[PDB]
Image (cartoon, rainbow over all chains, first blue to last red):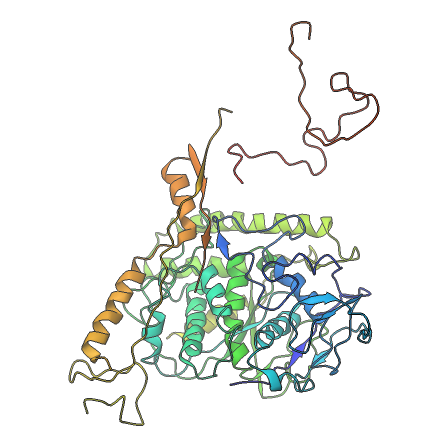
Length: 411
Length: 48
Length: 49
Length: 48
C-alpha cells in the first residue's frame, strides 16, 4: 500500500508549551482519549442545519484545531523514535491508541517541548512493522501537516487528468448523489482512515475526482448547466443555509478535459474557514486523497507563514513545486454568483441580490470569530480560535487566480 | 470476446461494450445501504 | 459474472435512487418551515458511509 | 403577598446551606440577573 508520511508539528505562535491543557484529552468525542479517527466524530449524528459548536469549542474547525496541537504534543515517534510523555500523558503501547496517564514502574522519558518538529515516519520502525493496525494515524498526521503548513486555512490539493473520468469512477460516484459536501467530507475521511488502501484504488481516484469536481461548483464553473461528467453541486440561497451543496446528477452540456494537468494546491486565506462547515469539509475532503497518496509534488514557498519556510519534504522552492492559489470565501462566492448570471441561471437582479445576502452571512462569520478570539486570547493556554488578527477578514489575495484556475480546469 | 473482463489482461474495471456486445464477466459494484427512518421530538412555540 | 446489459441497468437504478435521495439532516428544516415555525422539531440521524 | 402572590422571579440554584435559609426575603443581590455576563436565555421553543 503506502508507508512514508512526512509530517510537521503545529506552530506555537510564540507561546511556551503547545496550545492545549490536560482537559482536552478527556473531552474528545468518540473513543476516549484516542485522537486518531476523531475529527468528524462530533458530527456522527445530525440533528439539524445549525453548526455544532459549544462553549470551549467556539467554532466548526475548533474541534480539529485543538486535536492538532494535542496531536503534535505527543508525536516524538517518527521524529525521535522514543515515545516520551507530555505533562504525565503517554500512549498505551507501540500501536499508539488512546492516551493514558504515564504508567508507573517504567515511565517514558519527558518530551522536550519544541516548535515545528519535522516528522520522518521511517524513524519509527514499529510503524511499518504494524501498518494494518496503526493506519489511521497516517491519515491524521497528514491532516495536521496540511493544517500546520498554513496560518490561514488548510492547504489541500486539486488535480484532474488530461483525459475524461475512468469507467470505474463514473460507476462508483453514482452513489453519493443526495449527499451534502459536509457529509462527503465525513465519508471521504472515514474511508482513508481505517484500512491501508492503494494509491490506484477505485475509491481513491473517485474521491479525488469528487473533490476537484466540488471546486468547480464552489467557483461556479461547474453549475447546473455545466457538469464535469454529469456531476455538480446545486447551491441554495445564502440567506437560507449556504452550507448545503449535494452532488446532483444531470444530463446537460458537459465541459471538456483540459489540455494539461491542473495540479494545484488551494488555501482559504480568510479566517472565515474556521466557522464554515462547508470550507472545513472541502479542505478535509481533499486531504483524504493526499493521505493514501503522498503529496504529488512540493508546495510553493511563495507566501505561506514564516515557519513553513523550506520544510524537509513538504514545502520547497525549486522547480519541483506546485503553486498554491489561495482565495477568500466572500470574493469567491461573489465571483461564484457572477458565473451563474453569465450563463443565465439567475437574473441580473439576483446578481447583486445574492451578494448582499451572502456578504451579510459572511459578516456573521466575522462578527463571531472576532468575538471569540477576544473571549479566548492565546496566552491563556489553549488555541480553539487560532490568532488571526482583525486586520484581515477582507484582504483577498489571488482569489482571482483561483477562479481562473477553475476556468482552465474545465474548458 | 464475451469475457474481456475475466480473460483479457487489458480490462478496465467498469468498462462495458454495451451498445455492441453483451459482456458476461464484468465488475459490478455491490452496495450496502441502510435506510434511516427518522422519529424525533417536536416542540411547539409557547404562548409568548 | 454479470452481463454488461443487466449490470448497466442496475447501475442506472442505483442512480435513480441516489438521484432522489434526500439529505436526512435537512429534514428538520423542511418540517420547521413547512409548518411555519408553529411546530419546531429535532431528528437525530446517524450519518454513515 | 398578603393574598398569596409573590412578585419578581424565581431562582433555581442548588444552595445547600446550614444557616437561616430565607426563600422569601432574600438577603444580598440575586445571583445572575437577566442579560448579565454569560447568562443566555432559552429560545422560545426550548428545544434541546
